[PDB]
Structures are given as C-alpha cells and as structure tokens.
Length: 50
Length: 147
Length: 273
Image (cartoon, rainbow over all chains, first blue to last red; front, top):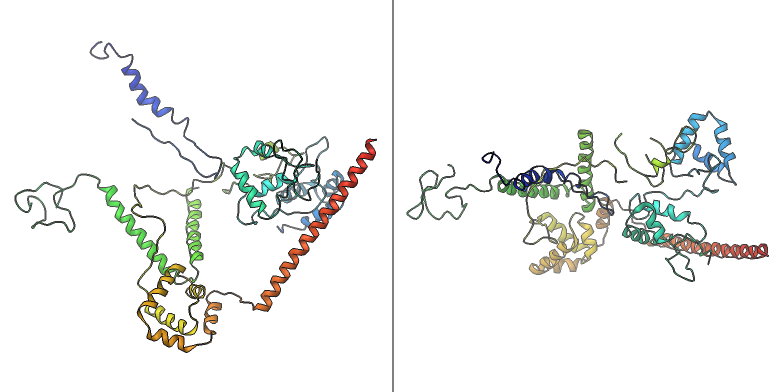
C-alpha cells in the first residue's frame, strides 16, 4: 500500500486531480465576456492547462 | 414601406380622434384573420403600437406622423431610433438620464453618442428646470412645461 | 539535403549537405535546423500573398475610377463571400429593427398581445459565419501612415504635361483628374516634376489652353452633373430659404404652444378655485 499510493497523498493526489480535472472544468463556467458597448466582441475559452 | 393600401387605411383611420372603435371597424370590414396578420405586419412596419389595458387594444396616440426611418440621420445603427422613440413619449416634463440608464440596461457612453448624434439634427431641444436634482431635461420640442 | 551537423571549425562543412564553400551569408541555410519549422515557414508565404493581394487591388483600381468606392467594392465582395459562408455553414436573419415589434410575431395573434414579454426581451444573433485560421504574425518596425506607390506610367506623365499645358497648378482638380491616385502623393509628384524639367513646363505656361477636354473627362469618368453657378446658386438660395422658413415656422409653433400652455395654466388656475 505504501509502495502503490504512499503515506502523504492528502495533498499530492488532490492537487493532481485539481490540475487534471477542476482547472479545466471551472473555466467552462466563465468563458463568455460579452460587453455593453459594440455588441460583437467576445472571447471563448476552449482549453486551459498548466 | 409600400406593402399594400393598408398604410393609407391606417392614415384614414388615424386622421381624426381615434379609439378602440376604429380598430373594431378595421377588424369589422374584411375577414378577421388576414386583417390581424397584415395589421401585425403594418405594426412591424414602424407604426402605432398597441396598449395593454382593461380594454383590448388602443392606438398611440392620435396622429399619423410616421417619422423614424430607422437607417438615415448620418449613420446606420438600430439603437438610435429606439432612444428617439423612448424620448418621444416622455410626457409632461421630460425624462431623466438615470431613467434611460435604468431602462434597457445599456451603457452610458452609448447614451452620450445618442446625445451627440441626435443633437446633430435638433431633436434634443431641452427645457431646463429651476432646480437640477438629476438633470430633468431633454424633452422633444417648444420648451413647454417650465415646472 | 537535410538537417545534419556536417562539420565546423576546419573547412567548409560537408558531411551530409549540399554546401561546397564558405561565406554562406546569402541565403543562410548552412548546417541544420530543428526549431520553428511550419510557423516560421508560413509567414513569408502569408506576407507574399498579402503583397500580391495589394498588387491585384492596385490593378483593379485602374478600372473603376473611384478609390474608396473600390475599397467598398472590395468589402462588398468579401461580404458576398460572407453570405456564401452563410449558405455554407448554416430563416437566418434573426435580428431586431428600429421599433419594438421584433422577432415570428409582433405580439400574440390569438386574442391580444401575448408575446410582449418575449418581444420586450440584440446580443442573440447570427455570428457563426466568418471562420479563418490563426497565425503569430507581426507588423512592427513602423506601422500606421505610409504611401503605397509604384513606378509611374509614362502615358500618365504625357497626360500630366498636357494637363499642365491645359489646366495648371490646381491640386484638387489634378487629384480629381487622376481619380484612383491620392492627394499627398501627387503633391510629391508636383515637386518631383518641378525639379527636373524647365523647358516643357515653360512652354506649358506659355500655351494657355482652354479647359474643355478636362471637363469632358471629369464629367465622363466621374459621371457628375456639374450644374452651373446660376443653377447651383439658385438651389443653395432655395435651400437656405426653405431652412429659414422651417426655422420661422418652428419658432411660430413654439410661440403658439407656449400661448396654449399659458392658457391651459390659466384654465387650471380657474378650475383650482
């Protein structure tokens, strides 16, 4: 068990799951940046990685 | 426009003092469904808009001016004739800048460019009050109320 | 051949390559490269196709004798390409108008205004039309103002000497006489032709030819009416008189509205007591 997973994995596994799933997932909830003046301009996030 | 003769029918029914009875007669002349469809088209051709009340539908208001033209003062944008129609029906004194900020939830510099582009052809002829709480100005014509 | 480190520090490097001498400064492929193949290869290609694009624009501008209208013809052609893309990728014109009746409907058609809550709700429109690939290009060094010119036509020079023999230093008329050039570049042409030649210019100022073929070219190539000073002066006087009559009618209507408002205020004061 210590060889496969290890003792200290309360931070490593959680941060790896963060940078693998959540850092790519929560940007899809905020991608549309439409403005008041000139109603044509936008950005759109399709990918994000560290 | 030039859809059919119903523009002339709208002029003849909007010549005098009109009410809901004029629309009763206009729906009374021909068959009802084609009249409702073509009248919806004519109201989509920059004409009088209906009024929601206890009664069914009213005109706005009594005259046949029909001057917005939607594309031609200096440039082409479908935002300016909207704001001109907002300041057509201001009422007795006028309309605030904060009131037109509150409606349509737009920016304030588009209101400033509306101010400039409509002041370029004299429709922002304002009447000034004695006090200035929130700039109760920018009525249509004639500097009429004076508080 | 390919990218391989042939040799260096001894002689002309030749292990696997096509070089046979030193001083490779001219084209500057020598040893081998392994960095930025396609993104740096497809940059001079993009620059070259944009330069050929501007050259074929300069060639098309000779036919239509209106510069900025040729630019609007170019953007009309590219928006014809845009409506072709509207045919390709995709009613479709879901937009608004100058009035509130926007859609479908102006309101409900059953009994009364039913869709007024939906008609009263701009930024939802058709935009997924123009898709183009990306790059990492640049426009630095100096960008902004400039002058895109060419080696000038000798027939244009003969026409210029005939014009200056016929209708002289008349900068606006000379800019209109060549209606696909511009103003500052023909001013540089004025000082350039003022530099090198005294003889034909002195004979040109000696000539004093009357301007009829110049007006002939300016009325054919531009299709302008050129109404005379009496007709244009009468039209300007009629426009000024119509504006003065409209201003006087607006002042009289404002005075009548103020008198009606004063009468209504007196009637309200009489009805208040």
